Length: 217
Length: 217
Ligand SMILES: Cc1cc2nc3c(=O)[nH]c(=O)nc-3n(C[C@H](O)[C@H](O)[C@H](O)COP(=O)(O)O)c2cc1C
Ligand SMILES: Cc1cc2nc3c(=O)[nH]c(=O)nc-3n(C[C@H](O)[C@H](O)[C@H](O)COP(=O)(O)O)c2cc1C
Ligand SMILES: O=c1cc(O)c2ccccc2o1
Ligand SMILES: O=c1cc(O)c2ccccc2o1
Image (cartoon, rainbow over all chains, first blue to last red; front, side):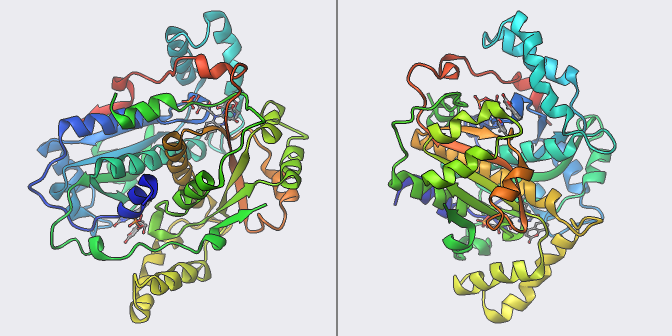
């Protein structure tokens, strides 16, 4: 099988973890750097990836399922790490300056061209919603990073469970300081599936027929 | 360098294509199958990938830049193929029926279980607009597929240019029948960069400091 297809046909959504296997620091570092290298509109990187690693952090995450989507709760303490994909509520010219400044430092643009580079920010200004927030534009960038992450995990042979069945309001309360100026609509548990109780590991993958999703013109 | 990091450090946004090189059908088939295998919330697959391959289709795509984002227009005819990432405006039970029916046909589930599988559709009603549109939920799923595609292209060593600088309104007119019931906010040109005029090929990649985007708890 072609290596790319093999990876995408073999990755799946784990439904039960093995609490005695942890992701190595070597593998976790690759995943985190892969997330950092994700592409985004105008190199905005309007995101923050929060890694729930410690027992104390896991308890806090565990508690965010207090009143909603409890079918996802058992994974928190059983898996190795949980990653929160946070997207910025509003993206300002100041946030953008952080990017442009770094670009001047990395030698991709000149300080003179920097001011000239601020014109690409108009693209952000046009995507400003009712309340003056850009969350409808920043959230999709974070999902792009998530797609990158899922492909990355398939290559490292690490199991995962993407989760939209979370409580964003309660997460913003529990991780108050960390999610300041951001929102979190999706989290990702990673680890190693349970050898006998992860029933999804044995089910066939199902997707729509090629002609139902692809059109060639 | 670690294979995953090498791929992500070496892929970049091409700013000029070589019109004499096309993507092979073998490579195109891998990319399209990779898009099809993308994960999505509840396996909804609320997307359609439209491939602009023929000269006639390229002309239509070329014409969608008549009003705006002219800086992106030259790539259309120069590159090999353009892929439109379309997301569904509203996701219904009939839409989910198609997913569940294919799941049954894929032996993933049984007809009896197909009836109980619709209980997962409750999560789609949770993203219904005041207008009844789920575009704020479907668009992020399409961006996840895009993140998957960008990683896939890095593995195949094919150049690309993601494009949000497009005209969704003009696209809806030009690709009237193909996009009925969908919207398209991002397209992707693929091909091979111009050997000497693609200036971005020689510029360093720039991303925010690890500490600025990643928090470990
Ligand atoms: C954005 C997103 C959110 C999802 N949320 C959940 C979730 O809350 N719980 C879980 O069990 N699975 C969740 N999934 C898993 C999907 O059901 C799964 O990706 C889809 O059925 C395709 O199956 P595979 O992932 O097994 O290929 C989610 C997936 C995506 C991409
Ligand atoms: C969603 C999205 C839309 C983008 N739109 C454009 C576009 O219209 N034109 C183009 O030249 N670059 C576009 N880019 C490219 C980004 O500027 C580029 O990904 C970011 O600067 C990081 O650089 P790299 O992609 O070279 O790593 C887009 C990227 C993303 C992910
Ligand atoms: O030069 C660019 C680069 C971008 O990332 C971009 C994004 C959205 C709109 C237009 C754009 O123009
Ligand atoms: O069983 C599932 C599968 C999903 O993909 C999902 C998505 C969002 C909310 C809850 C969910 O529960």
